[PDB]
Image (cartoon, rainbow, N blue to C red):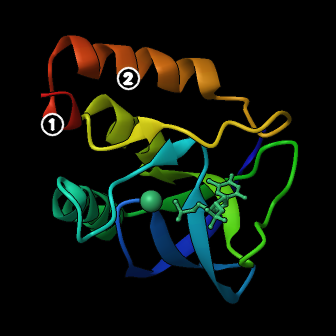
Amino acid sequence: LHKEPATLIKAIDGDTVKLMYKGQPMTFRHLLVDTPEFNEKYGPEASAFTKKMVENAKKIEVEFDKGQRTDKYGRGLAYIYADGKMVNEALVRQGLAKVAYVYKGNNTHEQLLRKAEAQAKKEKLNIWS
Ligand SMILES: Cc1cn([C@H]2C[C@H](OP(=O)(O)O)[C@@H](COP(=O)(O)O)O2)c(=O)[nH]c1=O
Ligand SMILES: [Ca+2]
């Protein structure tokens, strides 16, 4: 996989963000995770965590996996990096997302994220408390 440039347009919620990618505005959904909706428990905390990570970043990058690059809603499907730190992993490691939506062929970082979830769960963080 390869990281590609993008710039933040605006934070949306814990697992979606609006980025400019190849010069076009797109909503990106983070691969392999599920955050609570803003109206659900830890939803606002997940939204605030993602917002902080992407807004504070000097460099955003997107990395598509091997499979589908957009979903049925036209959202980009990618791993999102903020100054080299993967947001998808960071949310799981903080107990603010569950590993989820693991589809064959877009699951390159599944083991990495499951390791993060196990750590969050052992720590009883947030969703795991
Ligand atoms: C993360 C992800 C979601 N989706 C679709 C499945 C779910 O369809 P349904 O909308 O029919 O439930 C929806 C979940 O996204 P959200 O968690 O953003 O709601 O997005 C994909 O198709 N591929 C993916 O990799
Ligand atoms: Ca969600």
**Is ligand 2 closer than 8 angstroms to the Cβ of mark 1?**
no
Residue 40 circle label:
none
Q: Secondary structure at mark 2?
A: helix
Amino acid type at mark 1: Asn
Which quarter of the image is occupied by the N terminus?
top right
Q: Which residue is mark 1?
A: 126
The one nearer the camera, 38 or 94, is 38
Kind of residue sitting beneath label 2: Glu
Label 2 environment density (alpha carbons within 10 Å; few <14, some 14–19, many ≥20): many
Alpha-carbon span between mark 2 and mark 1: 11 Å
Give the image location of residue 17, x and y in percent.
47, 72
Task: Determine the image quadrant of residue 103.
Answer: top right
**Pointer 2 residue:** 117
Q: Position of residue 73 (x, y in %)?
A: 71, 77
Lower position in the chain sequence, tag 2 or tag 1:
2
- Up-down relation of residue 23 to residue 67 (above or below): below
> Residue sitting at 39 percent across and 21 percent down?
116
Where is residue 62? Give x, y as percent: 63, 57
Residue displayed at 26% across by 18% down:
121
- Number of callouts: 2
Helix, strand or loop under label 1: helix
- Classify 14 as above or below 121: below
Residue 46 in percent (x, y) is at 26, 56
Image quarter for ligand 2: bottom left
